[PDB]
Amino acid sequence: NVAHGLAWSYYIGYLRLILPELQARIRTYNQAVSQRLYILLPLDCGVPDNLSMADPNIRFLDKLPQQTGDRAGIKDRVYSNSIYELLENGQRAGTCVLEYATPLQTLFAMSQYSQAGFSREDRLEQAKLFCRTLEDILADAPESQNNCRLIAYQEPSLSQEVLRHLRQE
Amino acid sequence: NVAHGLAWSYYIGYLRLILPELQARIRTYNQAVSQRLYILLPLDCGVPDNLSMADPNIRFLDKLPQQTGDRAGIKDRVYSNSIYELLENGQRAGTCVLEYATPLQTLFAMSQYSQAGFSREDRLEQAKLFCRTLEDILADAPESQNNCRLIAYQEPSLSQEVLRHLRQE
Ligand SMILES: Nc1ncnc2c1ncn2[C@@H]1C[C@@H]2COP(=O)(O)O[C@H]3[C@@H](F)[C@H](n4cnc5c(N)ncnc54)O[C@@H]3COP(=O)(O)O[C@H]2[C@H]1F
Image (cartoon, rainbow over all chains, first blue to last red; front, side):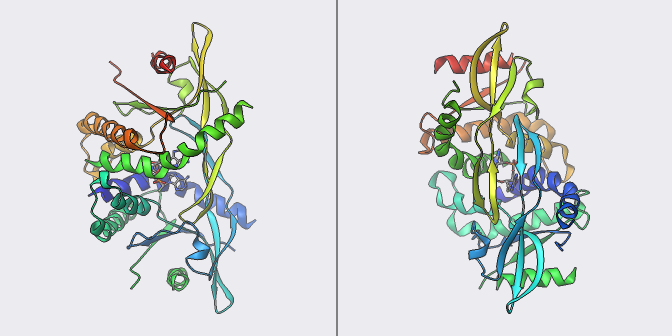
């Protein structure tokens, strides 16, 4: 159950820090980008570093203003987020702050390291536990007040998947 | 055993990324800072965000040149490190890149969240497991070739603790 600690690490070291400041950073940029942080959670733990090559309809636009803070002895640790435009039939259908959930890469990499004691076939179960644990945290989290939306999916169109969550907003 | 996953997360998401580039970043700054990344691992999981207030003899000097990379959909994710001067009896005794091991904060914060299922009295055991696991990884890690030194300590002078590791180098 490594995913339990990674989900709490994902909340303690990231979400609870950046979500309270997220609205103000989006308003600063707009002065339109949506008001939520959209987190992609592929359950196969396949996490590309370049979103534009995961789906051509996902196109990088710009970055939010950086958020900095002193963290564990590091002066001005930088928290940066990227804004993407979502294309549909050659039309701009939405604009939002979009990114993958990084700890899913940790699950994938542990499955490949023999010293990690992590079976290759346990990725799907741990990914589902990571999503379930993060859902339980964010549902009760005060830092999250319509601040982010989890997008979990099993791939048997990624931009169509994100747009479906956008249109409900 | 949440610490096992945090240690592998600490290596997969940080050390294996920044350690291969660390020497070149230090050489760029020197053109003197020591050649190793010194990681503080307090076993009580007490991790101040400001190193200068943990010990007055630890004084922030400057930052290394930033390292950037596309990470999980985030364009130009920033990896920054701080350089500290270590004072002894009013004398500059050493200069090195110094920081705490951030996941120890995750252990501490989980101990305070009732939903995390982490006992307050398990911090010391998990901290020791985190250090032990990280030691096993770095001992066999190709990315670490005289690139970093772990500084683990139980507090019954922090600058004297770091200087002892520096003088062996
Ligand atoms: N640049 C850095 N400087 C100093 N230390 C660093 C740095 N980078 C890594 N580390 C180490 C490795 C460990 C796991 O790293 P990971 O696998 O990327 O998991 C993260 C990620 F999913 C997210 N996350 C946090 N910050 C950001 C951000 N700025 N942008 C995007 N995502 C972010 O939260 C998780 C827990 O974060 P953490 O700080 O508690 O643990 C970190 C920390 F210990």
